[PDB]
Amino acid sequence: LPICPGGAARCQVTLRDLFDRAVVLSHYIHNLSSEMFSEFDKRYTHGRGFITKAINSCHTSSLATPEDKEQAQQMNQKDFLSLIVSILRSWNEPLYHLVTEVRGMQEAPEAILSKAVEIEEQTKRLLEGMELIVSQVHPETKENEIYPVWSGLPSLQMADEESRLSAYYNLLHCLRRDSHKIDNYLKLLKCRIIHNNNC
Image (cartoon, rainbow, N blue to C red):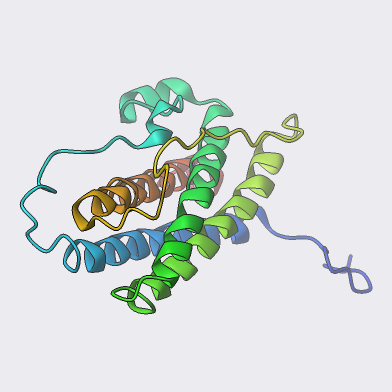
């Protein structure tokens, strides 16, 4: 039978194809959060002396994510698919503010904005790759897209460089580690998604 009868805008998609793109797409955000934050850390917090505190609030940490690889094996449930959606959506808002404040930042107008505008867009792409993957791996899932909330950056007019820096230091830094976590799950899921030998 024809792969795509006539011409459907939706047409059919191979779970492996989108999953493979979603697995690699997660690495792209890693570079964005890594370089986008590093360009900021070395620009506004260049050896500031106060950003050396081990700070990793990570609002998504509250999500029921796997504590370690051993627990992830113990999980083996739809929670993995739900956790990815919660993490990617949780950063959809925080990235919006980073782009708005950076857009008006004379010190960071297009430099950091270039990564901030593309980092918020790729994060949503993983969402679609995941929503079809979760809907294909677990057809029972009707529409699961619950994510944490946001309680940081109460006011973005903080002109203080030391205070405002914390505003993005907490977000951009956790944005990187979390982007890796979202990327890590696609790698583990690959083991039972396309090839038994992987991860």
